[PDB]
Image (cartoon, coloured by chain):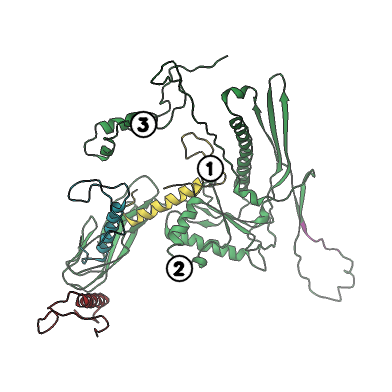
Chain colours: A yellow, B green, C red, D cyan
Amino acid sequence: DEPTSSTGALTEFVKKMRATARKLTLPQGSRDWNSMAVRTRSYMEDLHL
Amino acid sequence: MRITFNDVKTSLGITESYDIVNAIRNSQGDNFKSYVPLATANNVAEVGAGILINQTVQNDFITSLVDRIGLVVIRQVSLNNPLKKFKKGQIPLGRTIEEIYTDITKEKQYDAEEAEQKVFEREMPNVKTLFHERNRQGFYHQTIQDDSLKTAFVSWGNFESFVSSIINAIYNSAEVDEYEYMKLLVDNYYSKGLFTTVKIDEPTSSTGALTEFVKKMRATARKLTLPQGSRDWNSMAVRTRSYMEDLHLIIDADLEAELDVDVLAKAFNMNRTDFLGNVTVIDGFASTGLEAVLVDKDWFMVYDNLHKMETVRNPRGLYWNYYYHVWQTLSVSRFANAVAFVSGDVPAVTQVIVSPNIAAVKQGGQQQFTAYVRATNAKDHKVVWSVEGGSTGTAITGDGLLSVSGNEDNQLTVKATVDIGTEDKPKLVVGEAVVSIRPN
Amino acid sequence: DEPTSSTGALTEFVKKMRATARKLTLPQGSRDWNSMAVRTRSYMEDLHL
Amino acid sequence: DEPTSSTGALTEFVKKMRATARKLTLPQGSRDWNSMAVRTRSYMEDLHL
């Protein structure tokens, strides 16, 4: 919605980011987060925001 | 036998939302003014994403020569199934596995008068048995034309890395397939309906719903780990008890993030609120309302029977065929406790949150309140602002601006209300904020 | 207004007291805190309430 | 808005100050915080409030 609109939206943005990072860093991997649609995997120490 | 590609456009599967080059060109004081001083911006942007098909290109100085390839990189990945910790041991070749369970008996009245003839009578122990059988039999097949692949590489290291990448891929496919089979086990159990259902609200819609879901899960785990045992938490009911160290809870990333953002952080000494059992994070559930599943370590009865690899060679074709055969048995135990934790439908609007929860304003100052509505649907609803306890002259406008009268000694309660019901029957969702009045 | 009227009045009094102590302790001194209108400065360990 | 009108405005002022300080401290520089626009850079240890 908006990060700076309200605290209720800032916390929602934080929750969404945390969920996205957790599902990005999954042992089984996924192909829903790249333009090649290839089954890949990422790491927490390698992710940059 | 040469394969050539002609006049292939650079942007094959690119659907541009907007032309960045055109925006930079026709930028007048907007956010694109930063790229104006750049001189090679168009050339950078036209091949920044990457080109799928390579075309031979002569260099600038001598048209006869052709530009070469200066670097080759190979990408390798490794995938594992987090549910692998639920695997049991290995049975080499014994088809079918038998599970036994002896139940309790009833109490009898003592009577020596009738205990003279019924000494020899029998009483069956009331035993219950079930069986599991092999149900997974698959193989992965892949060919490698090593002799024909030597033209595409210059050094031997790249060739070896490519072969190792192929092997890694054939392993990763098996890993992901095993993970999907393990998830399909739980999906099948829920479809058959042998789970013990628990009706909850949607934990991701409101904070109160999440807290009540946490309370329900904690109570369920406490009554599961009881010394006396119970028959209410498993199919084909039998008196059994679990252990806290043996219980396992399976949730998803959205629920984990909402729990540890909205609840765990805002709660002091969160050891009294975190999940009791072990927590495992998976990639959602295929069922409609299945949110989290609470089972026991003995619930899974996955065994493996064969994990073999064979290689054959075709001298006429000059290639290798690799086969990876996986034979497994996938089954679950009906004597183990299981809780489904399902939820029903949700309303259009769940809750309204005012950004300043508590505030203090003077006797002449003004305050601004912002309302955030947690609506599941894509529609939007307008809010109505009101003040419950206040004097004359203190009022809130329709935009959320609260003005305080020049003199009052009371606590202000600013409320934002959203009406989702129909006419003649209003249903309201109210978000409150507490405002204090400092003297002037 | 009144120290004991309400919590808001009490905290306003606390803020006023702290600000007055700070501006009394400022090194450059002031002529606005004595009956002789003379430039002088006080000390935190020498101020009594 | 006003530091003294309400407690929320004080927090908003603190947020604005912190954002401004970070923007000043940004390494690549910015020509939007000085009387004559030159691409300049500041340091947190050198910033005084």
Marks 3/2: CA distance?
52 Å
Which corner quadrant holds the C terminus of chain B? Answer: bottom left
Residue B202 seen in render = no
Q: Badges 1 and 3: C-beta atoms under 8 Å apart?
A: no
Tell me the residue that label 1 is attached to: A41
- Is B277 a magenta residue? no
Q: Identify the subunit bearing mark 2.
A: B
Q: Amino acid at mark 2?
A: Phe
- Residue at 20% from the left image edge and 75% from the top image edge: C27
* Residue D13: quarter of image: bottom left
Q: Identify the subunit bearing mark 3.
A: B
Q: Amino acid at mark 1?
A: Arg
Q: Which mark is residue B44?
A: 3
Tell me the residue that label 2 is attached to: B268
Q: Are marks 1 and 3 on the same chain?
A: no
- On the picture, is B254 further left or further right than B301? left
User: The magenta stretch spans which residues?
Assistant: B122-127
Q: Nearer the viewer, mark 2 or mark 1?
A: 1
| Sequence-wise first label, 3 or 2 | 3
Q: Is residue C42 above or below residue D11?
A: below
